[PDB]
Length: 141
Ligand SMILES: [Ca+2]
Ligand SMILES: [Ca+2]
Ligand SMILES: [Ca+2]
Image (cartoon, rainbow, N blue to C red; front, side, top):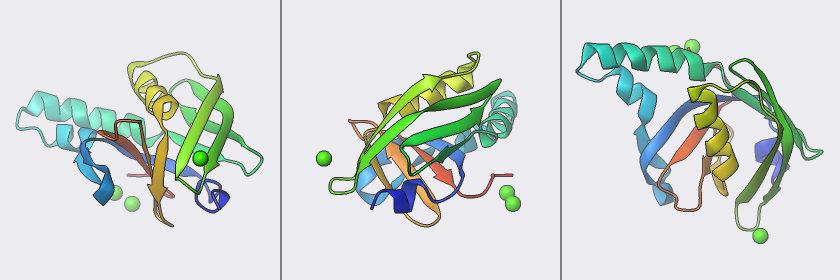
């Protein structure tokens, strides 16, 4: 069931993905692309963004609660998923002092309604399926 994917250990952010083809679990990784922009100043901003978002992680518990860590502190809340249609509903009860990257992460999780994944990855997409956030069970480095 859903606990076998969600409650499978700490999930660490890989990237935010755009131009998604949800059917095929593919898309364009935003900050890894930014770090390879041909404008060296934009590439520098992408490298800094990667170091920040790689620190973002979340742990879902089988009791329907979660905690996680982003800039300035912890997130907390509740979650439900349905394995019959691969849908999810995340609800925040605590967020730390805001930052641009925090706001992006919190919005992605708040808008998530579909999921897919496997023993390595978790992808969460909003209703339009044009974007997703991807996690892994290891911190990116
Ligand atoms: Ca359902
Ligand atoms: Ca690496
Ligand atoms: Ca490594």
